[PDB]
Amino acid sequence: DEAGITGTWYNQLGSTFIVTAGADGALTGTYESAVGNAESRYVLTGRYDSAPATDGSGTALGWTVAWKNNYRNAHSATTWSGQYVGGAEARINTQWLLTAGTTEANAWKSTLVGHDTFTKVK
Amino acid sequence: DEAGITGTWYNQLGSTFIVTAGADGALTGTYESAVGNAESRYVLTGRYDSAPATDGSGTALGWTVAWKNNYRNAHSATTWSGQYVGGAEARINTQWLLTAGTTEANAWKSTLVGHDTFTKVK
Amino acid sequence: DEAGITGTWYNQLGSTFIVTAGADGALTGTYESAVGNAESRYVLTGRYDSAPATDGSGTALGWTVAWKNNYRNAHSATTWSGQYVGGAEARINTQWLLTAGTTEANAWKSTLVGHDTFTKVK
Amino acid sequence: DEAGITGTWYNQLGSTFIVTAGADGALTGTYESAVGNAESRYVLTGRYDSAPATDGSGTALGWTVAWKNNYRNAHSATTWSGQYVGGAEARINTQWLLTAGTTEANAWKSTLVGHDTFTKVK
Ligand SMILES: [Ir+3]
Ligand SMILES: [Ir+3]
Ligand SMILES: [Ir+3]
Ligand SMILES: [Ir+3]
Ligand SMILES: [Ir+3]
Ligand SMILES: [Ir+3]
Ligand SMILES: [Ir+3]
Ligand SMILES: [Ir+3]
View 1: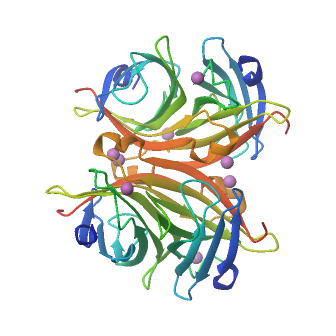
View 2 (view 1 turned 180 degrees about the vertical axis):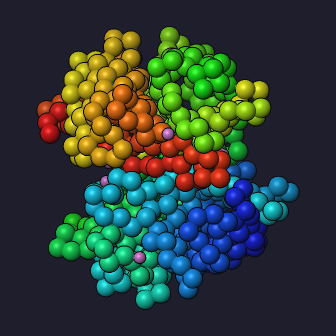
């Protein structure tokens, strides 16, 4: 799945996820969000299961973006957790957690949850 | 917070999180889970906000572990999203998503959610 | 939105959600899951915002099903949290948490997270 | 567990959860949040597993509050999903999803996630 995961992906929001999957389970690349307090590309790093089940199961993976780059700092980090499904309609189906830096008093409202589906076309 | 984050952390489950925070926002290290289909150390990578608010707010961060190493492959990945709070009782407060590789039919039950609190003592 | 919410809804899994919205914010009805350790109808109850923003915003709502009925007991409960969006393509977009009863030792793996989209056709 | 669940509970935020558990699996009561856009009591309804495992497992349950009452309308709903654990240090351990009513453009940031632990003392 190293071959299947590596490349450019697009989600339902119009965001662009560019990733290289290493032979070892490494994920590295950049993320550009179509929404939120974000501009241009942000570094991402993550991990994937580099020897997944050969019984038609998806390939577990995850990655993180910290929303600081040379343009902006949104004092937040998003992690996507999900699975890569290969084939003619390849998809990475994820759920994500976005945590903002907050005061201790506001910690209860620090974390957003959502889901993104990434495809090779878009 | 590069200085504050780098080091060994322990969660409420007895798991051990060893991390180095780079000047740039990189997180690298190893994770050893006290629970689940896990044995020994697993590679982790993530990101943190390397220029956080100076108004007492936490420092947003996240990381991923893919549960494959030389001992075991649990066909899953966990991402922790949260914030580092410094001081005498330093803490990393997180929520996490664990996605297992599944068939498409079982995708609805692919993802666990929980929360971990990490401290320097434990 | 009392009028818009009340009725039969179907999700992407083929599950059937039958609900009555009270003038007061009450939700009552039955849920039939197409998947999992479930058979036939289960009681549901919840709440909705009965005076939502008139600026095109969705209507916040939530409900719970405990997976015990006369046929089966799956020792679990699911809560859906989301919003109702009216119009020709009316939708209830949700994220859900399914907690199973567990021993204290297994509590870390007690809770599934996912998302369901409900429509009037299906 | 009907007997164990019924009563007044307090979370780590100082919020007050007053509930009656019906013989049938019904949960009814009021919630008063110590934090957020909330004042006084709000109606809650939910469900619990009224015949849980007798192997030391927790009792699955969930409930919803819509954040509208005679004082305020926060255009949001929270659902708590978790388990009741009985005994001398009885606890209801939950994870929750708070969805706000939003425009379709802002739906990606509509939902907060967190966790609450409720005890009989506090
Ligand atoms: Ir395998
Ligand atoms: Ir969605
Ligand atoms: Ir700042
Ligand atoms: Ir917990
Ligand atoms: Ir309003
Ligand atoms: Ir999905
Ligand atoms: Ir049982
Ligand atoms: Ir917390």
